[PDB]
Structure formats: structure tokens, C-alpha cells
Image (cartoon, coloured by chain):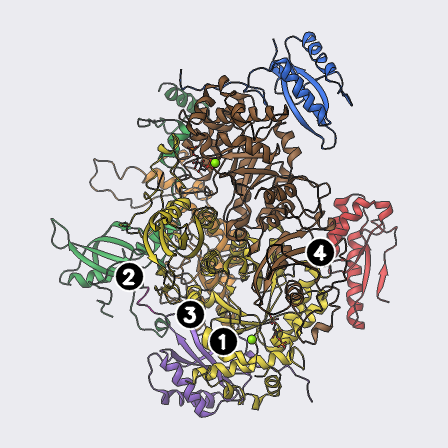
Chain colours: A green, B orange, C yellow, D brown, E red, F blue, G purple
Amino acid sequence: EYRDTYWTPDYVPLDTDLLACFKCTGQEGVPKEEVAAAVAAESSTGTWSTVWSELLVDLDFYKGRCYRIEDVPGDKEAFYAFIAYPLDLFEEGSVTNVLTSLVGNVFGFKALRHLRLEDIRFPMAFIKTCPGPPNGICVERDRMNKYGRPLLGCTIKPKLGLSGKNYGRVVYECLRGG
Amino acid sequence: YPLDLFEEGSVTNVLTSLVGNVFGFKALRHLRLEDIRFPMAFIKTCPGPPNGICVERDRMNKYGRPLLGCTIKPKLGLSGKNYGRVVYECLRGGLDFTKDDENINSQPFQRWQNRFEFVAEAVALAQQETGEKKGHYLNCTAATPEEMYERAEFAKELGQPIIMHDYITGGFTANTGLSKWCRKNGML
Amino acid sequence: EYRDTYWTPDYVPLDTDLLACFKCTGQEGVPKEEVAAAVAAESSTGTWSTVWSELLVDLDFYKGRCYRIEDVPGDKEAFYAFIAYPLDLFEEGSVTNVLTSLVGNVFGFKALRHLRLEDIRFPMAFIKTCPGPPNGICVERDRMNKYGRPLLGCTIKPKLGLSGKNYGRVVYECLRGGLDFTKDDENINSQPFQRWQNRFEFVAEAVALAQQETGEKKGHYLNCTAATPEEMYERAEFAKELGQPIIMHDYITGGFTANTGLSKWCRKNGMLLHIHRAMHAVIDRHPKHGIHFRVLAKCLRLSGGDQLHTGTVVGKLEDRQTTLGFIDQLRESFIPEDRSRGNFFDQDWGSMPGVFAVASGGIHVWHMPALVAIFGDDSVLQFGGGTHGHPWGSAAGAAANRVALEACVKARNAGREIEKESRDILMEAAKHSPELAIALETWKE
Amino acid sequence: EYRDTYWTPDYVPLDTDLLACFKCTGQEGVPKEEVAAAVAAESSTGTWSTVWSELLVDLDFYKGRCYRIEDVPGDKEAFYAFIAYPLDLFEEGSVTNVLTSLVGNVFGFKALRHLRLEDIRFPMAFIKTCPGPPNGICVERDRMNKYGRPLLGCTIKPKLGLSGKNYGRVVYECLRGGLDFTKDDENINSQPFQRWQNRFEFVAEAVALAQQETGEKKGHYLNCTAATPEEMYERAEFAKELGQPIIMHDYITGGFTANTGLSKWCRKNGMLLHIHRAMHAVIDRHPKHGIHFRVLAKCLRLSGGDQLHTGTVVGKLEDRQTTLGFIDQLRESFIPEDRSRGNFFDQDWGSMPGVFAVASGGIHVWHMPALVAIFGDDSVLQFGGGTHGHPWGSAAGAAANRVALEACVKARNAGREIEKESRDILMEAAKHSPELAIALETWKE
Amino acid sequence: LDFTKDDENINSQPFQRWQNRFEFVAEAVALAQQETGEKKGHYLNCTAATPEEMYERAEFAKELGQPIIMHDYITGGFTANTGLSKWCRKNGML
Amino acid sequence: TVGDYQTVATLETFGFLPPMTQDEIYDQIAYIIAQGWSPLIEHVHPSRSMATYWSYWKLPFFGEKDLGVIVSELEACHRAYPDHHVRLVGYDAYTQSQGACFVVFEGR
Amino acid sequence: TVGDYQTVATLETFGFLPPMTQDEIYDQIAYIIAQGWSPLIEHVHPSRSMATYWSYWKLPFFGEKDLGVIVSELEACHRAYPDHHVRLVGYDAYTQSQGACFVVFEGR
Ligand SMILES: O=C(O)[C@@](O)(COP(=O)(O)O)[C@H](O)[C@H](O)COP(=O)(O)O
Ligand SMILES: O=C(O)[C@@](O)(COP(=O)(O)O)[C@H](O)[C@H](O)COP(=O)(O)O
Ligand SMILES: [Mg+2]
Ligand SMILES: [Mg+2]
């Protein structure tokens, strides 16, 4: 247990992986490879401990690895850690699962003073399992017949107080006017 | 704040109103919500815990001491049967609960109907050998509420006493729907 | 309209494309680029005509293109045409749509005398939308507790005539003698001489009374093929209520729509699914026309089912390299490209579970060392008369195959050559079993 | 085990039997009686082996027997084997069972190099158990009010690319110009570029807005082929709720189990069913292997569906006698035996309604007098580019076929020879329509 | 004996409702089947005034684990007799 | 203008062709009779044109083998109803269907 | 009597064959190790024989390349539990499955 088993500088992410970017800065003195490796571990397998059970599994397959370290421009103690996750760690068409796995625990981990999830690359194998927009832009414009210009809206005020009938009174006036 | 601004028994509404907008307002550099006093008129509209401390100790028969748990590891990799292998060993040795990790939902390497069924055997075979009641919080967090209720009803049909959920990532709307499903069905 | 707008020799297929291989030969005189281009067109946009409407669309995006021409080795007028299709042309998790699009029309097109669909590369973006096997190999072995050896089966005979009670009589004898599965024949649906609620109920007693006497888990694939999908689900739900572990269905004659609805019913209800490839030789058999069985095995692994008939063992279907080729694709998770086994594409399945390879049709006791060396452990061996055809009955017949199987395994583990020392792996086994000792005398040799 | 226990030359088939014809040729040297006997065995009891269990049954009652051997005219090594099957071998109202039994296994059997199922005689006891067409010819003409002439259709193109709204744009133009049906192509299921709830809803507006402007009833076969049967019924029930008269399905790729479940959903809900014969050329095309399309037309008339593709018209599928043979069987109520049209059996349908004969694929305006003389009035004519390919658009294109059709009818009634005076039945029609007058100049001649 | 019969008159009279007759017969049949070691039965009369009532008695009798029932086809009609006869095939009753 | 096709309201069969000559009615009637069908005359107000049942006149000519009577029974329905469509039908008794159905007079 | 086959209660694999010699255990263990699997010893009371989980002894031999230790760890489990079945297993970590599973000692 000292990591740099999650720091793979030679790895080339698959097209089925789920990539992530973290803007991080860790404790004073510890090198960047170790502290980004800790982010790789604590967001996937969170290990190694020493158990009999952790040898019932090929854990080099489900491990998340950090393949690139880059420096934040304009800051020195911070860095960008790019980390790759196998597609098997997640449930299909579940976005509640993809966040519970990624940001579920690493933010409490103690060695990091600052950690920010900046971006995620989703693979095409994951995108096709999700529902997506029920209609979209081009189908909404079809169903409403509104072309060539942006749409316009209003938010009814006062927020607090109007009866069901006075509400509809003010809704009727904004709509009938444009 | 007057009591009329909020919906009854809705905690999704009390936060949407309070912290919904003020944090973006520009004149404040720093703002932290420290505390809230709820009135007794609001508390009585909410569901609350499905059981509580004193009812859980009754249903499990555990008195006079704190309870003990373990979280099964490795989080990533074990089949439905090896999972139940490690669940069986911690329970038969002295603990009374085991935990699904937050990541374990229904991954390709271990679907949830296979994990739910082999845990049900590791719990039932350690409850009889020790002579004590034992459990395992099965993670019923899902992507839809139709899916969450389906896992909850699978777990109750297998005769299990307790389940698990992630309320910050799954949302208070789902957490409150699950919390009131647990009262009609007698689950923890 | 003359094509070579579908002949793109410079194109490099995406990782989201759906590739296909066609073994083709067209009319005399026309160059190969034109005739493979016609296959590219007629299986996607089937055009260009001349219409006002075909300009409302960017049709260079939805077109299917042919990026490689290769020559069949051993033949001159034929060639291999590799064609790429965009992922947008297909519905997600629909295998009924992927075949309706590909083989729906091109086979009738007139310029081709011979056309054979040989292979398809599915992309990982498409695989993840499909249901797949309801359980798989590793989950079936878990639920049944059967490790280290192939499974054994029998098909009850006579197919035509037995009442619901005599059926269960013969099911009880094969199970109590050493096998672990029995099979409903493909014909058995709900005939006048044996309705299905009477067969389902007396089998449930023969299975439950042999599971307790042996101390091992046993099963019987009950045929839930019907005329309607409302009827199919009704038989499935009867069988689950009787506490049965596995059922059966015919996917080529009952259709992929029904097969996929049943395959996803089995996941919510925790049942196993066994698939029979009836009417496969109508399509797959002739070497220049139709689809290879390899492609119908990939579509089956994508649609569902945990076991699939591969047959056929007299003495086997025969080359072995072609059979070992698509046994890899039914079982492995990544299959490289090898032309000897007829894999034209690198196929990655990711984390989708495998499917049991069922060998069938006319096995006898001297075929074990050749069916353990060829198929491995994730196989089912199903005889029809190998069990029943024993001079002392159906329980003494099953007891002879279970002894000859476990003698061939334990000799494969210990480093011996089973398919080469077969006679001393068997005659030394009959020294400790009079049931096998008489079976070796009958089916000589 | 040597057979000629299945070669009964003296047997006279019952009126409850299910007869079959096979065009066969076996290995060199073996007599014809043995090789046709092997076809009798392998398609019924597939025996005799030697088992204790095969004596628990009277197997001379369930055996299939071959009562006639006849020689193929024009060939020597081939022969016709007529085989009779007892009515007890099959499930009632199940066409998935009748094919699984017959063609399920015999095609793989090794002693036959070539085997083709040519015909089947169904008995009246079996016909009355099946659902049949949901409506038929005479009920469809009632519900749509279309009498005295064939119906007209078009298939919307481009197949790949159009949004839900542009689709309905092109559907609206062909209908408002003279046709009465439009077709979803077989590929159109629910692709990313056009989901099905968006196509179904904008077509419902193009059909309802052209029905009111013309004053005639109009339709569009919406494709309800899906990956599951739960999905198929969902699209069917969406389409009925939108007030649509007709839908579509692919029975060869979606399976007879799904096709029969849909066919009986259409009777309780009063909808029409149009059938597409996708992947037919894989099986039916080669003259010595597989099943004839005639047999798959009989099974379709028994399973359901009111219209069925017969094609294919460039300039036609070609002989005409073979096509007119199984057009009789799709439409008539009693069909005698005639060898020129390839009817080997007298087939009586009793009171089961007929099925529309759809001609398709590449018709143009000069093909009308040959497609009215060949097919008659209970036909649908479906062009893909015949309507759309007109220099002035898709509404002026439909207006030219509807004028050329009604000029060919009214000349058939009045005693003229349409397929022989075609040029004066058309040039005298273009004198009173500038839409046809320009269509005759394009597709010359 | 191996069967007993409800008389044709016995439907659900005030002196003996049918849920009380059905339940105490189910005990007399199950306690004689075990003492003799032979299978025994009693045809319970599921003739009623409505078809909703007839199916209700049939489904009570099947839930009590009974093998056989009874019906009057001339007075209850062939329409009811055929609906009951096809209910018995899906539920495995005599 | 070419080519701007205008949607036109039609009846159904023979609607796209010009109105029939007296000699054309002869041959259609002769064909209807030579198939063994029964002629039948109908009419409606052109507004009720999409009703499922038009109006008879007077009873179907069951077993009539003379076309010189039907051409005179068509001017009677027209003169009696000079603002009605006048349809001509051919009843098929064995199939329970209609072998012919075309409007003769369009409605003055 | 011939031929009256009597149903016999067996474990599962190698159950129909006679008990293995010491030399046979050597070769099965050597095969298990040469595939890269992990050996694992279990035992139960012969009445609890159909439980889903037997009882370990003591921990799976992760990364053991010597078969002279496993033949001595099998007499220990047997001597400690002289009325138990003694199973021998071969753990596969990449497939999460078992490549071998056969009872060695039958339970005195
Ligand atoms: O042809 C034979 O050799 C058998 O009859 C066995 O004969 P024996 O009974 O004499 O061994 C085969 O089992 C069947 O042909 C098909 O197999 P199955 O019916 O098992 O599917
Ligand atoms: O090849 C042709 O002749 C057409 O393109 C018509 O050309 P034009 O547009 O020039 O007449 C045919 O319609 C299509 O091939 C198939 O028919 P469809 O698409 O109607 O099914
Ligand atoms: Mg053999
Ligand atoms: Mg043509």
C-alpha cells in the first residue's frame, strides 16, 4: 500500500473507457504522481488493503488508472490529473451510478485540500444505453411550429400569493401579447 | 419565514426555497447555511424515520451495546457467488451487519439479481449457525424510481430485513418515496 | 445511376460502424467494383433514382460503402466484399431490425447469382443496448452448482405418443441414473395426446423426486414455444410457479421478436433459457447461398439464451476449424481475426456473458474422448438414444455415460491424451462399473 | 433399421391427413423407394433405433408414410415423393409447429444431396383451427369503399434520412395526387434520425389532411416490426389510437409466432395487416434447395395478414404460369390440381377469406396493361419511384398512374385487348391529361 | 369409497352457506386421504345464479386444494357449462 | 401554369377521366350484365357524398338481361333528382361484393 | 443381480469412479497449479452436503507453486475433522469461476 500501481504513464485509453479530469492540489511535499494516484484509487477500488478476499478477483482489470499529469496554467501547486475507468464499473443507462462512483467518496479523502471535477468523456457504448432528451431541438420546433428565431418566455410574478384564478389571469396577459 | 411559504411534508421544497437562489446572488462573497429551526407544525406533516432506534432494536433483538458492521471488499470485481462467500465469513464470525459499497449497483461483472440472491443465502446460513439475527444492506439505488422499487420488492421477497440508498446523489424525492415504502412494508 | 458512389477504397471504418462480409459472384463481364457497389447500395439506400425528395436529405451520410475487395482463395469468379454501415441506420437493442435491413432485400436483387453473408462486426455501442444472455455460463454454474466438467443431457423418446404420466416416467429414469438435464423435443407443444399442463405437472414431480434421491440439482427444459406470445408467457409462468429452473424455445421458427421478449422475461424472473436451432439447414447449409450459422450465433448471443444447439456429432458435423471458430464467438469475450476458423473481423464482446455450446445428435460412449478434446468444459452433451439405448434401461444407460465422462475428464487433467488413448481411458473404467462394461460391448467400437 | 416400413404404395391418404411434396435426388446407386422412405422417416418419427421405450407406443399410427413416387419431367436422377402425415402430429392453429415438424430436421439429413419442399395439402380439420386473415379482400373493400379496380400504393423514399416531419411532407404529396396507400420501408423501425412516435404522429396528419381534400379514404402502412412483442403491440396500439386503418409487419424475420399474435390482435381491434416477405430469396430462390414461396404463401394465408408481397415486376419476376399458380392459392376458395401452375394437390379453403396480391418493385406507366391483364382487380400495385420520379413532383406523378390505371380498366371492361393495344389505351388518355402526357415522354417506351 | 357428492339442491342455503361447507369438507377429505393412504375427493357443487359467482366458488375450491367439482348443465345452461369446462383445463381440475 | 398540380375532389373510380359518352355507358352496362352481376342505381346530394349508404332507385334489377331498360332507368333517376350524383353498381351475389361502382351523372 | 441398476448418492465430479490413489491426487493438484489456479480446501458434515457454502481450511493458497504442501494440508483437515468430506477446489481469478472441484476424502 503506497500506490503508483494506479499511475500508468504509458497507458492509452480504450474507446470504451470513461475518462475524467480533476483539477487538484494535495498536501505540501508529496509528489504529484502519488497524489493523482490516490485520486485514481479512491474513486474506483479504494485499495490496496490486505485481505484474503481481495485475491479472489483480478483487480488489475477493474482498477482505474491515471495516464496523464498536466500543469494548470497560471498556478503552480495545482495540476490536471486525467484518469481512465473501465466500462464495466458502471450500470447501463444509469447516471445516478456514474456520479455515485466518481464523486461519491473521493471528495472526503484527506490527502487532498482541493479537488474539482472539470470534465468527463463518455464513450459511445455508454451513451446509447441512456434515454436522452425526450424530444430535442428539432422535434420541439416541429411540434410547436417555431422556426428561424429564438423562443421567448416569462416567469409569473408574484411567486407567492396568487390564487389559481389570478395566476391564470396573469398567464393570459403575457401570452396574448407576444 | 412564514409557515405558508412551504409545502407540507416536502423537504425538497424547503431547500429549493431557501438555498435555491441566494447562493448565486452577487452582493455576497461568502454565505453558509448553518442551522434551521423547524416548527412542530411542519414536523408532523413529514414521514420521518420508517422505524427508528427503539423499533430497530426490537425487530433485531439487540440491546445494551452498539451494533457492528463491515463493508465488503474488493468493491470492484467479485461475482455474485464470491460476494456471498465473503459476506458469509464476516457474519459467521461476530458481526451483525454487512454493507454493499456505494458503487455496487448492477455492473456487468455482477448483476443485482445475482448478488441479491447469493447474499440471501449467506445471511440465512449464518443466522442459523450463530443463533443471532444478521443482515446485509442491499444497495437499491438505481437510475429510475421504477427500478428502485423493483429492487426493494425483490429484497423484501427474499426475506431480508434492511436495504440502503444514497440520498444526496439519488435525491430527496426518491429518498422520501423509498422511506414511505419502508413503513408499509416493514423494512429498515 | 451507375454507382461507384458506394465504392470507397480509401475509407477507414469508424469504431461505431457495423461491418459485414459477403462472399459474392456476379454476372459475367461486369467488374467486381461495380457488383460489390451494388451490394453496398441495395442493402442501405438502394438508390440513386431521380426524385425531388431525395435532395431533402444528406444521403452521403446514411449511405453504406464498400471499402475492401478481396479474392476468395480457391475460386476465381468469387470475391469478398467488405461493407461498412453507419450506426444510425439501426434501432437500439433490436436484432430484428439489423437483419431486416441487411438481408431483407439484397438477396433478391438480380445482378447477383450467388450471395452469402459470412460475418458481421458489431460495435460496442450497439452491443450495450441489447439484452444478451439472461444468465450466462458462470451464472448458470453458480445456480446449479456444477463445476469442472461438461453437463449431460438426454432427449426423451418416443417424441410422439406418450401421455403426461408416461413422459414423467421416462424423465425420472434418466435423471435418477446420472444425467442432470432432459429435453422436450422440438415437436412437443400441446398435442391432443398430451396437453401441456399435464406434461408440465408430471415432469415437475419426476424432477423433484430425482433431485432428492441423488442429492444433486436436476432439470428439464420445458418447451414454451407456442402460437401466440400471450400463450408463450403463460407456459413460462406456469413453469416458474412449479419451481422449475430452465425452459426452451425455438428462435428461428418462433422469431427473434418472441425470442427477445422471452429472453428479457427470464432476467426479471431468474430462469434459464435453452435455444433450439430448428430449420437452420434451410438457410445455412449450402456453401454459396444464404447466411452462415456464425452470423445467426452472434445474433443469438445478442438477443438472449444461455445454451444453443451447435450439434451435430455423427461423427461430427464437420471441418473442425470452422466449428471451433464460432464456438469461440459464443463463449469468449474477445476474438481475434483468423481466416482458418473463418473470423473475418476482430470481435470484442466486452463484459457480455458467454453461451453454452450444446453438442447433440447421435453420440455414444466411444465419442466421449473426441467430444471432450474438441469442446472443453463449457459444453452440454445431449444424446437421444445414447442413454435410452442401453440393454438394461434408461437409468443404467445414463450411469454408463456419467462414468465415461468423468473418466475422460480426470484423464485430461492428469496430462494424458484422451482422444488418443481412448480405449484405456474406457476399458480401465469398466473394471469398476458393470454398467459401462456392458455398454462398451454394445456400441462397439 | 433399413426402412421400407415407411414406403406404403397401397395406402390411400385420409381426408384428415397433411400431405407434402418433395422434389428430391439422393446418393448415387440407392433406389428411390429407400431414399423417399428416409424422407418419410426423418420428418416424423426419425427411427427405428433399438430402445425399450419405443415399444411403449403404437408407432405404426404416428408414422409418416410415402404413398407415391413420380418422376420429375426433364430430369432423371430426381423424383417426386408424396408423403402423408396423420393429423395428430401437429398442434391446432399452430403454423410454427407444422414447419418445425416438417422442415425442422430433414434438410440436414445426410443421404439427400438436394431436397425441396414444393407443396402441402392442408386438411379442412386443420384450417378451421387457424385464425386466417383478419379481414380479407371483400371486407377490406367494404371498410375502404374501393370497388371495381386494383388499389395503388407508393413506398416513400429516401428510406434513410428524413425527419418525422419531412416524411409526412412526402406522404402528403403522393396521397393528395391520386394514390390511396403509402408504405413504410422495411428498414424503418425507430432509428436515431427518426423515432417512431414522431413518424407515427406526422403521418397521421398527412393522411388525415389528404383524406379530407380529396374526399376519398387514404392510408399508410406503419411498420410495427420491433425487437420484442411488448414493443410491437405498443406501436400497434399507438397507431390505432391515432385513428389509422392499416399497419405492416415482416413475418419471415419477425417470425410466425409474432405474426400470428399480431394477426389476432387485428381482429379484436378491427385493423388491416400488410405483410412484407423480407429475406425470402435466401430460402425460396434456388430451384433445388429450400422451400417454394408457394408453401410460405399458404402458411401466411393460414396465419393472417390481408395483403402479401408477391412482386417483383422488372419487367416481372418470371414463368407466368408459376406465379399465376400461387396467386390462385392466395385468393381462391378451391384450387384444382394443375401441374403447369405447379399445384400438386387439390386445395380447398372452404370459407376462409382471400389475400390481396401485391405487385411491386420498379413499375412504370407502360407496365399497367401487362399488370392489369396478369393480376386482375384484387391486386395492389406499389411503385417506389414510379410516383416520385416525375419531373413535376410526387403529386403530379401519382396523378399520372391513377389516370393510366383507370384508362386500362375501362378498356378491359369494354372488351378491348389491353396488353395488346397498350399504346392507344395510353396515348388517347394523355389527350385529356397533361400530367400523363409528360410521363409518357420520360419513361419511354 | 373414493368420492362423495354434493346433492344437486345444495347451493348456498341459509342453513349451510357454501364457504362453510367448502371448508369443513376440505378437512374431511384431507384427513381421510392420510389415514387410508389413498386419494379421495368430493364433488363440490359450484352451480350458482351468476357466472361471476360460479367462478368464485370454483376458485375457492381450487385454493383449498380440491381435485374435483360439479355443475348442472341442463339447468345452468351450455354457455355456463362451456365456460366452466375451459376454466378446468387451465387450472387442472376435474 | 406548369407544373403546379392542384388537388381535385373526385368520387372514386373513373373520377380522373372525363365524363362518359352514352356509348361508353352501353359497354360498361353490357360488361356488368355479361359477368352475371345485378345492376343497381343510387343517388345522393353531393354534400352527403361520403355517407356509407346512398339512396336506392328503385330495387336492384335482379335477373335483367336487357341493357335498353337500364339506360332509360338512368335518365329517370336523373330527371327526378337533377341535383344528385347518379351511381351505377354491379351486385355480386356469390361473393357478397361489388364488381363495379362508378358515377354516371355528376349532379347538375 | 443383472441388470438392476440402483440409484446411488454421489457428490458430483469423479463421484462415479473409485476413490483416488495418493498418486492421482498428485497429478490433479499438479494440473490445478499448472493452469495458474489457486487451490482451496473445504469440508462439511455429510448431512449438510448440499449447503451452498462449505467450510474453508484455512485460506486459499494464493500463489503457491508447491504441491508437497497441499498434500500435507489435506491430511490436516482430515485428521482435524475425521467425519467430514474433504473437497479440493481450484480458484480462477480472471473468470471468477472454479476450474476444478472434486471430493478427495469421503468422510469416515
Ligand atoms: O442412431 C443412433 O445411433 C441413435 O438412435 C442411438 O442409437 P442407440 O440407442 O442404439 O445407441 C441416436 O441416439 C439417434 O439417432 C439420435 O440421437 P438422440 O435420439 O439421442 O438425439
Ligand atoms: O429503377 C427504377 O426504374 C425506379 O427507381 C423508378 O425509376 P424512375 O423514378 O425514373 O421512374 C424504381 O421505382 C426503383 O428501382 C424501385 O421501385 P420503388 O422505389 O418504387 O419501389
Ligand atoms: Mg456417432
Ligand atoms: Mg419495369
On the image, which quarter does residue D318 sit in?
top right
Q: Which residue is mark 1?
A: C371
The reply to whether dot 3 and dot 4 touch (C-beta < 8 Å) is no
The reply to whether dot 3 and dot 1 touch (C-beta < 8 Å) is no
With respect to residue D443, does F80 lie above or below? above
Residue F68 picture location, percent across and down: 73, 14
Look at label 4 and name its amino acid.
Asn
Q: Is residue D312 left or right of residue C326?
A: right
Label drawn at residue G8: none
Look at label 2 and name its amino acid.
Gly
Look at label 1 and name its amino acid.
Leu
Q: Which residue is mark 3?
A: C321
- Label 4 vs label 1: CA separation? 44 Å
Q: Determine the chain carrying the residue at label 3.
A: C
The reply to whether dot 2 and dot 4 touch (C-beta < 8 Å) is no
Give the camera-side residue of D175 and C82.
Answer: C82
On the image, which quarter does residue B94 sit in?
bottom left
Q: Which residues are magenta?
A: A58-62
Q: Residues within 10 Å of mark 2 (few under 14, many from 20)?
A: many
Q: Determine the chain carrying the residue at label 1.
A: C
- Label 2 vs label 4: CA separation? 55 Å
Whether marks 2 and 4 lie on the same chain: no
Secondary structure category for the residue under label 3: helix
Quadrant where the N terminus of chain F sits is top left
Judged by depth in the image, the label closer to the viewer, 3 or 2, is 3
- Label 3 vs label 1: CA separation? 14 Å
Q: Which residue is mark 4?
A: E91
Label drawn at residue A64: 2
